[PDB]
Image (cartoon, helix red, strand yellow):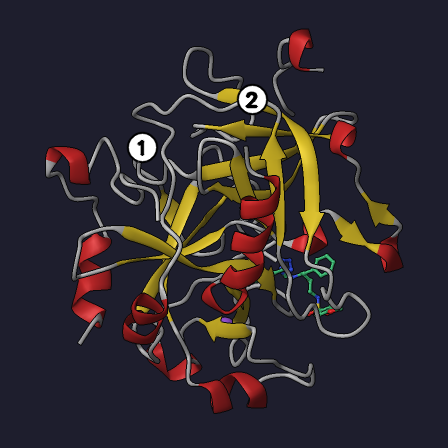
Amino acid sequence: DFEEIPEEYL
Amino acid sequence: IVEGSDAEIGMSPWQVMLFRKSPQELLCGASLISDRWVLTAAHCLLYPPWDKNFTENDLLVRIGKHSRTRYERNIEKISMLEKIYIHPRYNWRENLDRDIALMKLKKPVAFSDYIHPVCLPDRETAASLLQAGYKGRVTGWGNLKEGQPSVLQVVNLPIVERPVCKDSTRIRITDNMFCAGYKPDEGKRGDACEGDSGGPFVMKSPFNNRWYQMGIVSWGEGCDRDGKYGFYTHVFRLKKWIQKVIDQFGE
Amino acid sequence: GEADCGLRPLFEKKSLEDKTERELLESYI
Ligand SMILES: COc1ccc(S(=O)(=O)NC[C@@H](O)[C@H](Cc2ccccc2)[NH2+]Cc2cc(Cl)ccc2N2C=NNN2)cc1
Ligand code: NA
């Protein structure tokens, strides 16, 4: 559903 | 939001999405009150009956958003939480009395056309604007019916007389809550719904042309039911606590 | 309250009104 956010945030 | 409309770009620049890190999902709304503080509902972060008790590292906030699902490259900013503060007398056992929490960001968010803080009310602003029949505005990416919006939704709703709020529900209402929404005989409709909790109920002061957050989407029995109303945390009534936290723990 | 709080860059700052804010004003009787 949600577009991948940049992995830096995770 | 039920029976709302698509927000305009930059219409609610204090809007914050509370976003679970894994699984990656929308938890609640929230609001930006300074470059490092976000306001939301305590129940979005702490609700023991459902085994909900988030720590700082479980969560992100996404600020400056319009689209619900897309990563809004060059527009939204995503922030990590330094610290969560839940009101010490938040009543999760009974009726969500004092449903309020603050989140301090690890780093200040940069303001932009899409990111800008809302004001918190003074005593006089609350006394002037929190009147039955006066309309406020609710925004969120929650469900459209008791399904999900492509973009931020907006609905304007009238504040309701306290006896009418009390008589709509079996839940014990407190002075830290107010209710809002249209009556069955008013024809117009609208409500928050699932995913909207923690977001802002705002009013635009006709005295100084500024938006003030008067409420936080707190609880409601179903969404947009006839004879039922949304309940909102009374922000001014808890501003002493808000200021205490910010004064002690602000840099 | 913060100096510039509650004034939106794309609306109040530029003297543009959103599509439904008048409904709010009209209710402040
Ligand atoms: C402990 O206090 C309680 C008070 C009320 C209720 S309830 O009215 O039975 N349920 C409220 C619940 O649907 C939700 C708030 C909540 C979420 C998670 C844990 C505890 C409470 N209501 C959110 C909401 C707010 C508004 Cl203003 C309008 C609609 C809704 N809503 C209803 N369904 N989905 N969203 C439950 C416990
Ligand atoms: Na209703």
Residue position marked by numbered label 2 in the rendering? B107
Of residues B182 and B34, which is closer to you in this image? B34
Of residues B58 and B241, which is closer to you in this image? B241
* Residue at image point 87% right, 60% down: B49
Mark positioned earlier in the residue sequence (2 or 1): 1
Rendering coords of residue B159 (x, y %): 39, 74
* Residue at image point 41% right, 21% down: B110
* Residue at image point 68% right, 54% down: B42
Residue position marked by numbered label 1 in the rendering? B10
Check disc 1 and report its element: helix, strand or loop: loop
Of residues B178 and C5, which is closer to you in this image? C5
Callout 2 and callout 1 share a chain: yes
Mark 2 C-beta closer than 8 Å to ligand 1: no
Please count the marks in the image: 2
Disc number at residue B132? none
Rendering coords of residue B167 (x, y %): 57, 90
Amino acid type, residue under disc 1 in the picture = Gly
Chain of the residue under the numbered disc 2 shown in the image: B
Dot 2: few (<14), some (14–19), or many (≥20) neighbours within 10 Å? few
**Which residue ends up furthest to the left in the rendered image?**
C15
Residue B137 in which image quadrant: bottom left
Rendering coords of residue B189 (x, y %): 41, 67
Above or below residue B201? Residue B164 is below
Q: Nearer the viewer, mark 2 or mark 1?
A: 2
